[PDB]
Length: 426
Ligand SMILES: [K+]
Ligand code: NA
Image 1: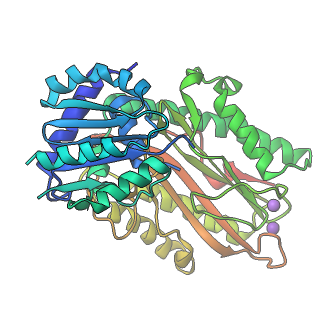
Image 2: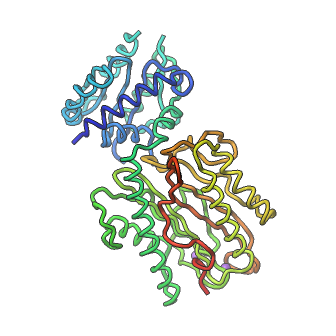
């Protein structure tokens, strides 16, 4: 089950980073608590379990101290975690202590024991991912017990963000596999499906496009992918939008309205496949008999997106990359600047959205080799030429997954020309 070599390497990386940047990124914490809810959203806590152990551990609390790691979990998970005791000892000198919770027990006594151990290891500062809302009885109780302890509590989300920021070669491979499928689905299913639907003047709901796209992702054979299907999931329900109803937030959901493709129309599709828990993303906009404003805006958006990608190089600030897009729009379409999305995307990995790596004007984080980005840039609520049209107000979106290498930036969702002529239909 558990890759012990990966566990050791990553536990060492974690303890090293924690120690190296204790005050700066880890809130001066002496101990760090992570907790995952019962099976049911992306959680940074879930990402840590996946990163460290290669599997989710729902309804589990894990607490790292200088010399121990305490886990509160089911007997079944505890029998599994027995195997990492020796590797944890031999890697960072820590003792794994397993506290088994009975199914009908609330785990209260074990939480008290864990809290006593934290105190023993020595005031105490416990780091947690503060922005996470506890879900379920276990996490509710734990949060209350931490709150009611004497401990100082520090947000350490930025520590985990830094830790997950630069991917190993293995992780980059999984993202490329994911991105290959993502791109293959867009190119070999979505584009073909849309073309057929518009050709035959079919009626199809956005939610049907969503479901059909899901099916192809989960059976990548349906587009000749050759990825182990057991390793594939969807990052989010595919997004299809048209007919004047757009929403560029990543949480947008495909509605039950029919795809709209009459004159002066645009269609937005965003899809992302996940491979061995590593996410990828792509988004394309297709234009049907586009009017001059829709056409120009798309050309400008493409040039702006390419400018972000071209600016994501080791040593450059994420903010400079975002402002590269702004500079393009300011030059070529100054009146459209106000419609540009305020973000050009985020880091991406186990988490679909790495919030600490948001490509925006306020993020002065420096690009490093091994970072991976969902470069996703749009125009929101532009006005088309004929205001009597269904797309009187419209939006546009382009997204790709890129890998930052030392010597070049790889666009791993490259599936063919994004130029207007290739995404426009008449
Ligand atoms: K329209
Ligand atoms: Na529509």
